[PDB]
Amino acid sequence: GIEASLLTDPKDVSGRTVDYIIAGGGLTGLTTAARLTENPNISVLVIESGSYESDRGPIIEDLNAYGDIFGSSVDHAYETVELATNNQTALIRSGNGLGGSTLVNGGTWTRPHKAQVDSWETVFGNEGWNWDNVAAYSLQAERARAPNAKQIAAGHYFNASCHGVNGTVHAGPRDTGDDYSPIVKALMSAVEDRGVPTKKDFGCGDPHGVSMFPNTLHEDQVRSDAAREWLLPNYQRPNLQVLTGQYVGKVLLSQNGTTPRAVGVEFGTHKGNTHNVYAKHEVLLAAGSAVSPTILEYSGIGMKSILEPLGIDTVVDLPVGLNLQDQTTATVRSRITSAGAGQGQAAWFATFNETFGDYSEKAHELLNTKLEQWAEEAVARGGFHNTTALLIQYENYRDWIVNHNVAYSELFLDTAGVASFDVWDLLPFTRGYVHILDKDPYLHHFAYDPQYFLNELDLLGQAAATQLARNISNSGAMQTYFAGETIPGDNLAYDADLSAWTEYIPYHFRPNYHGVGTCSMMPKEMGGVVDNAARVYGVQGLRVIDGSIPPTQMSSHVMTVFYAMALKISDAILEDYASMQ
Ligand SMILES: *[C@@H]1O[C@H](CO)[C@@H](O[C@@H]2O[C@H](CO)[C@@H](O[C@@H]3O[C@H](CO)[C@@H](O)[C@H](O[C@H]4O[C@H](CO)[C@@H](O)[C@H](O)[C@@H]4O[C@H]4O[C@H](CO)[C@@H](O)[C@H](O)[C@@H]4O)[C@@H]3O)[C@H](O)[C@H]2NC(C)=O)[C@H](O)[C@H]1NC(C)=O
Ligand SMILES: Cc1cc2nc3c(=O)[nH]c(=O)nc-3n(C[C@H](O)[C@H](O)[C@H](O)COP(=O)(O)OP(=O)(O)OC[C@H]3O[C@@H](n4cnc5c(N)ncnc54)[C@H](O)[C@@H]3O)c2cc1C
Ligand SMILES: *[C@@H]1O[C@H](CO)[C@@H](O)[C@H](O)[C@H]1NC(C)=O
Ligand SMILES: *[C@@H]1O[C@H](CO)[C@@H](O)[C@H](O)[C@H]1NC(C)=O
Ligand SMILES: *[C@@H]1O[C@H](CO)[C@@H](O)[C@H](O)[C@H]1NC(C)=O
Image (cartoon, rainbow, N blue to C red; front, side):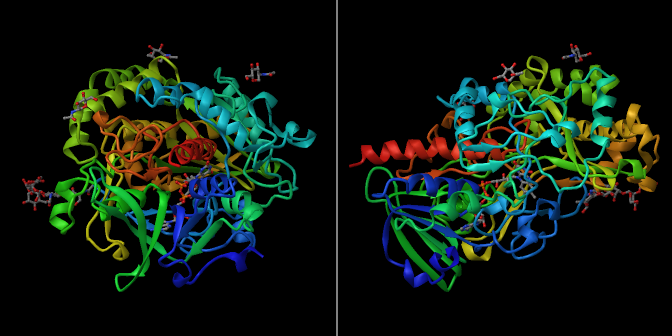
């Protein structure tokens, strides 16, 4: 079985040499490892801090048990600094084990707006990173199943052109076996009354309106986590090696040439218990957006002003750990009548004007006039280092909103006994950072600051979207099922205005756990860390391939793009491999 093939003893890899070392056995790391070992000549070693969890039981395998695993040893639970918005620390849920955060997530499978991905090439200069290319790799990864008569009847719509059927990641409609709740169709009807679209397939390139969606699970409803999809079918390959239960602490760099070269990694569990392993070709970082940047910083790749005071010699000065972008989530929950019983999830991808409603003119006024003031403030807070380059990101977001009308907020609906909305502003203007606070990697002492709500439009947009969730819960056809709000319930008057909501939100939100950007893929002059093939600037044989590299947020759930991203980067690595013979 797979468990017997996994390595646990540090001495089984210590001192050996492999072609590629992948730090982190998560979504991008395992997709890359499987892809690279298709060629029998390439040897790959994956080093994962956690272990095999995919067959544990329903706590991992059933998507309906979402949330039960939090706080366990399968959850890294990274703590933020004390946030300025509320003076509290927040926990960042993140999977710890083979498959990473795909072990503990909600399984939602959707794609962004075409214009968002196209801007990676046209605005950020990443040649080849456009919707057409990324979507093609997304389809290649995908193994979707169309909905059946019962599922269609509940509200599903599936455009066959927009889904791959021959790929690797099993995706299909979640179906617990009970009846589907009629609240999903009631919500659709309520938004249809306001001229909002319904049933568009959210994998097609224009996520807008209210629709149901596929989930990453097999037809028998077992979670399609990355280790089940990419590692389980290929674990017997003799060139694929997986070491578990150990942390990668830093990259080993040789400086006896013009340009520094990555030759291996140092791994371990504590400062007194560390081992080295070497790479013939390249070291690939895939430890997650909260960790990959810190691995660079421990290794002497990052800002001198951060590293020098810690007693670390700066080999390459780069803006590692800046440009962190995560979203904020708040909840609106209502009791329903018995008539609404049944399973089902749906989401409203709402545009800027749909979110703000009659406040749209005022919200547009801010968008048009404060971009520069906002960029200066975020830079003064340490979220980014170049005001001009940050202004360009903001102008790009303004373009998406005013010219492309992309979805600005997401209202995610859960039923199964209640009407529960989790809401989030998809496009934050705040920028945060993550930096180490000690030289020892195994101390795990770092400062992670997303700077939630320190940009005024993020606060206004979140409050507007959450107020919209309360409004739509007791509107049109939903009024038949509404049996009283429970959250906020007594904690915020039912007729609260927008300014009241803005005062309530900072005390009642959670991270959305979608942090991207800490090793941003954009030109060096725009504040980038990696180039368009994910190579770290100024270093040979080192790439960062995970959620740290997307330079922007997106109007969707990110698994469809991250699986595509890893496949596209793996092709680039395969070409370079043939070049270095
Ligand atoms: C997160 O925590 C940080 C602190 O760790 C918070 O930041 C601190 O916030 C406090 C305010 O709550 C602030 O203290 C004020 O400093 C001013 C000087 O800059 C003072 O003028 C002010 O004193 C007045 O209020 C006091 C409190 O009631 C009185 O005891 C005092 O005599 C003063 O009273 C006069 O003024 C008040 C109105 O100011 C008036 O009602 C009275 O009649 C009287 O005329 C405070 O001492 C700190 O400077 C802030 N910074 C630091 C580092 O401490 C931050 O707000 C927290 N964030 C959140 C979201 O909670
Ligand atoms: C609670 C939650 C809900 C989500 N819901 C959705 C959803 O519904 N739909 C969706 O599309 N996406 C969702 N996501 C996001 C998606 O799961 C992640 O964006 C994706 O898994 C990130 O992939 P990655 O390869 O960057 O990192 P990960 O998958 O996190 O993997 C990084 C890996 O590195 C390991 N690691 C960490 N530190 C070290 C170290 N020092 N050395 C070695 N290994 C290390 C970690 O244990 C982990 O396995 C959610 C995420 C979370 C946390
Ligand atoms: C399906 O999606 C394609 C986009 O590739 C679109 O052209 C078509 O109109 C959509 N709808 C149907 C009914 O196929
Ligand atoms: C959004 O609202 C603003 C202000 O009313 C308006 O100028 C714009 O045309 C609206 N609609 C769209 C789709 O942008
Ligand atoms: C700041 O970013 C701008 C815009 O990308 C770029 O022209 C400039 O060179 C950057 N400045 C520095 C000093 O890096």
